[PDB]
Amino acid sequence: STSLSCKQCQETEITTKNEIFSLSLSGPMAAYVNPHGYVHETLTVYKASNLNLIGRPSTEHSWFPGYAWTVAQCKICASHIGWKFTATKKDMSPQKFWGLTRSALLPTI
Ligand SMILES: O=C1CC[C@H](N2Cc3c(ccc4c3OCC43CCNCC3)C2=O)C(=O)N1
Ligand SMILES: [Zn+2]
């Protein structure tokens, strides 16, 4: 229903609350530890748009075993919004989703 927009440029829709989903047995809203020990608050959604991808998928320090990650940035302002996760194996489900930085969106949830 509600849009989630890039907090930096404000006008740009990234996804909607009805794309919010739970992977495996995790809640949709979760915090994970980055390689330097920062606690990073994310939201998992099936679909997102107005994002560029940077770099190639990587499984290093993957918060989601089985999935690789690729940095995702706002197409308009280049602010880092989150990551695209893609499955490393063909029988996994889903094959793709997005883990977005909560604090990079508006409204903030
Ligand atoms: O599944 C997920 C999504 C990506 C998320 N990452 C990945 C990552 C984050 C921060 C810094 C870095 C990084 O890899 C590259 C690096 C570490 C080596 N030095 C350069 C910068 C970060 O937060 C993570 O740990 N897990
Ligand atoms: Zn933006």
Image (tube, rainbow, N blue to C red):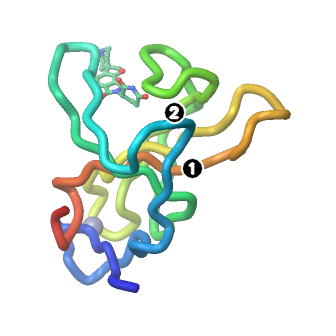
Q: Are marks 1 and 2 in contact (CB under 8 Å)?
A: no
State the separation of the CA atoms marked 1 and 2.
10 Å
Name the residue rendered at 43%, 25% in the picture: 63
Residue 48 located left or right of residue 4: right
Hey, which residue is sitting farthest right in the picture? Answer: 90
User: The disc labelled 2 sits on which kind of residue?
Assistant: Trp
**In which quarter of the view is residue 66 placed?**
top right
In the image shown, does 83 or 27 lie closer to the viewer?
Answer: 27
Rendering coords of residue 43 (x, y %): 35, 51
Residue 81 located left or right of residue 92: left
Name the residue rendered at 22%, 34% in the picture: 40
User: The disc labelled 1 sits on which kind of residue?
Assistant: Phe
Q: Which mark is residue 97?
A: 1
Rendering coords of residue 106 (x, y %): 20, 71
Choose the circle earlier in sequence order: 1 or 2.
2
Mark 2 crowdedness (10 Å alpha carbons): few <14, some 14-19, many ≥20: many
Rendering coords of residue 39 (x, y %): 17, 28
Q: Which mark is residue 68?
A: none
Residue under circle 2? 69
What is the count of numbered marks?
A: 2
